[PDB]
Image (spheres, grey):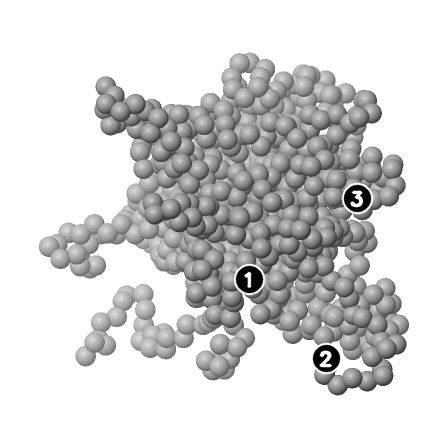
């Protein structure tokens, strides 16, 4: 595809393209993209199950064509591959072939009882703390 | 600068890295709660398997028969040692003592158990039942098993005795306290072997059935008898007695009650599923799922099927039979299916459900149905539909998803999100090459190589070498990558056990180092007056020691929330 | 020579040191600050450990001079502690060989601890 620049991938273009695709799908699936999540925990709404909140591949291709960010033609295989890259990151999920929907965890990641999934909210331990648990330990 | 091997052996955990996590954890817990004698006995039983009293005497230096018998009594009362009495052909009878993870996990989960008991029965309204529930559960866990009459013999107030009896009945009704018996002290494998041999002998000799037919019939009879024996604790046979005065249900006086670990692990699994659902479907829908799981929790399937510990999985047909039986019991149990009308009565006053849904781009049944349909239509199988409007939790299909999600997010938190991406990429298409990874997962090749090299060290990615020469040289062969779930899950379970054990070891070392100051501070006259009766330096040392101990226990709780998923 | 061949990614400058640290550098997110619920859970842990430490089932580690003084009177006894044979055992749960050390015919007292309501840990 067009990702190869001088024989290697251009990670900045990858990040920008993935971010704009994820934002488009986030605007599709939620009632208002990144609007209800402001003042989120008290007042946030979601779509009814009968609502087709999923965004198909054709809509994403049309949006990225009209956005003029890619600057080249995009085969549906290419947008499908980068959306597979997104679903590998757990940013979104696939419910039907050529259909995707943004997961709520990716929305919460941009900004109580302990959970492993909200690990970004946790703060690192202060220095000179002896009783700190390391994942690399027992293997080093 | 350079660090000497003296400094490495002193300030690091190199000496503890060579210990098995099971033995290290069990010995540390027993040495922390009980003494060093019980720690030696438990460690020797873990290292050598089942042992007799004579073997324990001859294997441990510094202990005689009476000391070993006394510490075995102490361990057996707290249910840390299982036993089996067997008779040889010559007629000699010998008792062989095992170790059971149930009692050690009870010691490990004790404060979590007390908190779950306090929170679960909705005594959050006021204070006196908070005191009584906490004290009775703490006494039950500390003494292993106690009778209600012996507990009430220490109370002189009639109203207090009545409230304690009512609270004991309330605990017994909802499955948290059960009747202790010899079933909780005999091994599962030995019980199944006894049942299978008994049902094998009862088959008449010179039968028309072949050997395999006899084995199958014996297995069926052993399975139904084993199911009856296992479920016999949960039939509420200790509560049927009514008091001499009418209109009061009481627990039997002479029965011995014990804490039920399976119900507590069911509650922990429910909490894990609620936490998983909080990251996929909203917060109000998370509350609805929470209420649904709390309602269908006592009758939910057990965390581990005991028949899986009987060595019966060597037959593939037995594995399929166990899977089908699990799928059947998670669905056709009468108390597991639920409707919106059933959940309508259990919703709290604060929960609203009014404006939580938009249909187009007061605890009513339709809103609950919409929330449960959102739960059922999610990518994760939180709920499934048997018939339309009836919902049940798919415990057979939801728990590998929970394990995979927890494992992937732990890797994301430790090794980075790129590690999550690479692991899920290798998982989605099962066997891949480096170029296929680079094409499918869009990131730099050197980053791919470094990330998979890091992931290989933790059993996350296994290298499959395909040789292209007569000798399997690494230069000419091609290396593909696959992701085996079981190896990685077992490795991380062992790692979390080692981390928990090392944390407990550090806490015990700190307490042993500051023992004099902690003994001075914990005295009856000193306590409550630490500022007046202690020097400022000793006060600051006590400050640091107690803060470090609280941090140790908090990290232990957080590890336990992260480790029980792989014990499911 | 054994030194000539190098991988493409590496160079001569960055190899030949072999400094593998003995100290880990990848922490879990569980090392955050403690909360109120976690503080109550921790003091529950401490209370349970203490109440098992001084209970009848401890079995601990494996100046009482023989000289007699008049100061022996007016000096109180330390503690009449509960022993292993002063507990109401359920004899159906124990093997027959352990009956000798439990005192099957002795006085029976149930050591019931009292729950500490307040988080008495000095911060």
Which is nearer the eye, B69 or B321? B69
- Helix, strand or loop under label 1: helix
Residue B37 visible in image: yes
| Spot occupied by residue B432 in the image (x, y as percentages of width and height) | 30, 44
- Helix, strand or loop under label 3: loop
Q: Residue at x 86, y 77 (%)?
A: C73
* Other residues around mark 1 within 10 Å, as few (<14) / some (14–19) / many (≥20): some
| Spot occupied by residue B99 in the image (x, y as percentages of width and height) | 49, 51
Kindly identify which residue carries mark 3.
B153
Which is nearer the eye, B200 or B511? B200
Q: Do marks 1 and 2 share a subunit?
A: no
Q: Which mark is residue B118?
A: none
- Helix, strand or loop under label 2: loop
Circles 3 and 2, Cβ within 8 Å, touching? The answer is no
Q: Residue at x 60, y 39 (%)?
A: B180
Measure the alpha-carbon separation of dots 1 and 2.
25 Å
Q: Chain of mark 1?
A: B
Residue B487 is left or right of residue B517, and the answer is left
Q: Quadrant of residue C7?
A: bottom left
Measure the alpha-carbon separation of dots 3 and 2.
37 Å
Kindly identify which residue carries mark 2.
C64
Sequence-first disc among 3 and 1: 1
Kindly identify which residue carries mark 1.
B66
Circles 3 and 1, Cβ within 8 Å, touching? The answer is no
């Amino acid at each position: 595809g067009p990702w190869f620049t001088d024989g290697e991938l251009d990670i900045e273009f990858i990040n920008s393209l993935l971010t704009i695709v994820w934002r488009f799908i986030s605007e599709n699936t939620f009632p208002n993209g990144f609007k209800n999540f402001e003042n989120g925990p008290k007042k946030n709404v979601f779509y009814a199950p009968n609502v087709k909140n999923y965004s198909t591949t054709q809509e994403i291709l049309e949006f990225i064509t009209a956005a003029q960010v890619a600057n080249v033609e995009l085969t549906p295989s290419n947008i499908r591959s980068l959306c597979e890259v997104l679903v590998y990151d757990d940013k979104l999920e696939k419910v039907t072939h050529d259909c995707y929907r943004v997961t709520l965890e990716s929305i919460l990641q941009m900004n109580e009882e302990f959970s492993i999934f909200n690990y970004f909210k946790m703060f690192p331990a202060s220095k000179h703390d002896k009783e700190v648990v390391y994942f690399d330990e027992w293997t080093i | 600068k350079l660090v000497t091997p003296e400094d490495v052996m002193t300030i690091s955990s190199l000496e503890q890295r060579t210990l098995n996590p099971d033995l290290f954890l069990y010995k540390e817990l027993v040495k922390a709660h009980l003494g060093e004698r019980a720690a030696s006995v438990i460690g020797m039983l873990v290292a050598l398997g089942r042992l007799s009293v004579r073997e324990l005497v001859e294997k441990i230096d510094g202990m005689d028969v009476d000391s070993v018998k006394t510490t075995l009594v102490s361990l057996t009362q707290l249910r840390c040692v299982k036993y089996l009495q067997e008779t040889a052909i010559s007629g000699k009878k010998t008792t062989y003592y095992y170790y059971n993870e149930e009692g050690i996990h009870i010691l490990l989960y004790s404060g979590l158990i007390i908190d779950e008991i306090i929170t679960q029965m909705r005594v959050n309204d006021e204070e006196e039942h908070k005191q009584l529930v906490a004290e009775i559960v703490q006494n039950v866990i500390s003494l292993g098993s106690l009778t209600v009459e012996d507990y009430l013999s220490s109370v002189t107030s009639d109203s207090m005795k009545y409230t304690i009896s009512s609270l004991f009945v309330q605990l017994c009704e909802m499955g948290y306290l059960i009747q202790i018996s010899k079933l909780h002290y005999t091994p599962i494998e030995d019980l199944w072997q006894f049942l299978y041999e008994k049902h094998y002998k009862n088959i008449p000799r010179n039968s028309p059935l072949s050997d395999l037919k006899k084995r199958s019939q014996a297995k069926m009879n052993a399975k139904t008898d084993f199911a009856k024996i296992i479920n016999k604790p949960n039939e509420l046979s200790q509560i049927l007695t009514v008091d001499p005065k009418t209109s009061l249900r009481i627990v039997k006086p002479t029965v011995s009650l014990t804490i039920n670990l399976d119900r507590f692990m069911k509650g922990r699994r429910s909490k894990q599923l609620i936490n998983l659902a909080k990251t996929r479907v909203g917060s109000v829908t998370a509350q609805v799922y929470k209420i649904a799981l709390r309602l269908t929790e006592q009758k939910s399937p057990k965390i581990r099927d005991p028949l899986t510990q009987t060595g019966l999985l060597q037959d593939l047909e037995e594995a399929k039979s166990f899977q089908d039986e699990a799928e059947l019991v998670e669905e056709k149990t009468p108390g597991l299916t639920f409707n919106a009308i059933d959940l309508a009565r259990h919703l709290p006053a604060e929960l609203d459900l009014r404006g939580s849904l938009l249909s187009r781009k007061p605890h009513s049944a339709s809103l609950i149905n919409s929330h449960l349909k959102i739960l059922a239509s999610s990518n994760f199988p939180f709920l499934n539909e048997t018939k339309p409007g009836v919902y049940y939790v798919p415990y057979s299909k939801l728990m590998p998803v929970l394990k995979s999600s927890v494992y992937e997010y732990v890797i994301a938190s430790t090794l980075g999100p790129s590690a999550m991406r690479l692991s899920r990429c290798i998982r989605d298409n099962k066997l891949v090459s480096e170029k296929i990874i680079n094409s499918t997962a869009l990131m730099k090749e050197k980053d791919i190589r470094s990330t998979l090299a890091s992931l290989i060290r933790y059993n996350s990615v296994e290298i499959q070498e395909v040789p292209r020469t007569a000798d399997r040289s690494a230069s000419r062969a091609v290396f593909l990558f696959r992701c085996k779930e079981t190896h990685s899950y077992n490795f991380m379970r062992q790692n979390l056990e080692w981390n928990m054990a090392n944390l407990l070891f550090k806490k015990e070392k700190l307490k042993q180092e500051n023992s004099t100051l902690l003994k001075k501070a914990n005295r009856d006259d000193v306590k409550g007056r630490e500022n007046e009766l202690l020097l400022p330096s000793e006060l600051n040392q006590l400050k640091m020691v107690n803060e470090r101990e609280l941090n140790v226990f908090a990290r232990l709780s957080r590890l336990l929330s992260l480790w029980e998923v792989f014990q499911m | 020579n054994y030194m000539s061949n190098l991988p493409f990614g590496l160079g001569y400058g960055d190899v030949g040191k072999n400094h593998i640290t003995e100290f880990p550098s990848i922490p879990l997110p569980i090392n955050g600050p403690i909360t109120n619920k976690e503080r109550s859970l921790a003091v529950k842990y401490i209370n349970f450990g203490k109440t098992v430490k001084d209970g009848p089932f401890y079995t601990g580690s494996m100046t009482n001079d023989g000289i007699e003084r008049y100061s022996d009177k007016y000096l109180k006894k330390r503690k009449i502690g509960i022993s292993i044979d002063d507990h109401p055992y359920n004899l159906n749960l124990f093997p027959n060989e352990l009956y000798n050390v439990m005192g099957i015919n002795k006085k029976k007292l149930l050591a019931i601890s009292k729950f500490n309501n307040a988080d008495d840990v000095f911060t």
